[PDB]
Length: 129
Image (tube, rainbow, N blue to C red; front, side, top):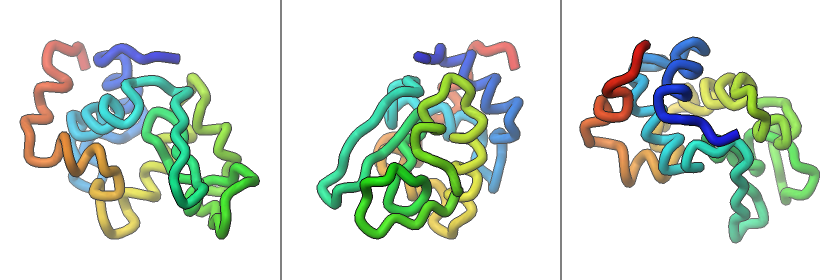
């Protein structure tokens, strides 16, 4: 499913992401935009053989099991395909564990390079939340 900007903001808000660990909703929406372009089915393979999955491009080396990644850890304890669902609940629950890991949102390279230090508030502008 390809989410609309405001549509995603509301689902994320409903799932408790607004201000989770101090990151306002705009940060999460901006991250989704640049990580997957709001597409739940996005996948991208990496040089180390791992693959990123879903709306928030969660990596298979540490967070989910795809059955084909060298040295995977499956910290969120879910098959990676669960992260490609139209229902973002799994992606949100796993993202919550990732952001609490210590590096905060820096774990998402697109966030670090394209959202961090920008007016992320623009991403929820005009939405009925």
